[PDB]
Amino acid sequence: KILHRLLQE
Amino acid sequence: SLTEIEHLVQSVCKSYRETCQLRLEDLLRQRSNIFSREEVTGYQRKSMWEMWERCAHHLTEAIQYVVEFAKRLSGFMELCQNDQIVLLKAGAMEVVLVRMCRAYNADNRTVFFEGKYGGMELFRALGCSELISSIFDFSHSLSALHFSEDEIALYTALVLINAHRPGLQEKRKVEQLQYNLELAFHHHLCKTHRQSILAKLPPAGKLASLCSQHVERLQIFQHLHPIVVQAAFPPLYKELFS
Ligand SMILES: CC(=O)N1CCN(S(=O)(=O)C(C)C)C[C@@H]1C(=O)Nc1cc(-c2cnc(OC(C)C)c(C#N)c2)n(C(F)(F)F)n1
Image 1 (spheres, each protein chain N blue to C red):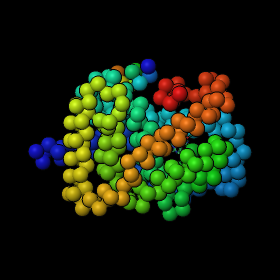
Image 2 (tube, chains in turn green, brown; image 1 turned 180 degrees about the horizontal axis):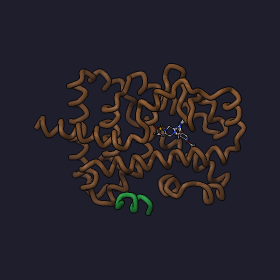
Image 3 (cartoon, rainbow over the protein chains, first blue to last red; image 1 turned 90 degrees about the vertical axis):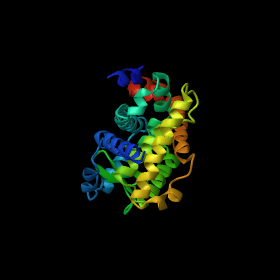
Image 4 (cartoon, rainbow over the protein chains, first blue to last red; image 1 turned 60 degrees about the vertical axis):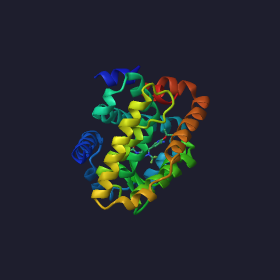
């Protein structure tokens, strides 16, 4: 979830 | 191509310098700033859950820089998102543990923590004596080798790009990336006359043992204080470890 968002930032 | 290998070395070292969280010079310049006995006692008197919360916070912020390090590795962003997550979940804490050797002073066996250097007795309230001592021992081994900034860059890239992680979909692709990073690391050691450290690096499974201990101790702490973890641990920390 958070890693998903961090990788897309 | 030797040129392609050396371009990878430069790229990895640059990616690490941009994401190293703390410049090495800032850590070295603070080495004489050491916690007093009263400050050490204050840390020891803190509750277990408050020391765990603060330490989990510091680990979470350090992990965030490791994620940015991964994002600046060109081969890493070529992997599918499943494999990106697998590598980060398995290797991010290992990278942090390697990075900790820069914050460790082998001359007096202290580590930089919350603005000053302190011995391992500073962390007694955690109830993680074995984990903390093993981290100190691990950091002391890398410090004794004078692990350079470029060596840490290339080594932590290899820690992350590990084709043996269970759950990888494009295993062959990670294998190729790992081999190129191994060539880059070993080429840099050869060019800098540092190949003698190969036999002196910590064995395989030592880093995994540290990460397993961290998860095991967290499992115990979460069993003891489930609401503390739910209410006060950082969400990224829980996503990674619990
Ligand atoms: C803000 C701050 O103080 N900083 C951030 C910059 N790093 S840093 O650049 O090193 C960066 C790469 C961290 C140094 C330092 C730090 O955080 N040091 C630190 C953290 C821990 C630690 C604490 N709690 C742990 O587990 C508990 C949750 C049970 C574990 C483990 N496992 C490890 N230790 C150790 F000496 F005690 F290990 N020292």
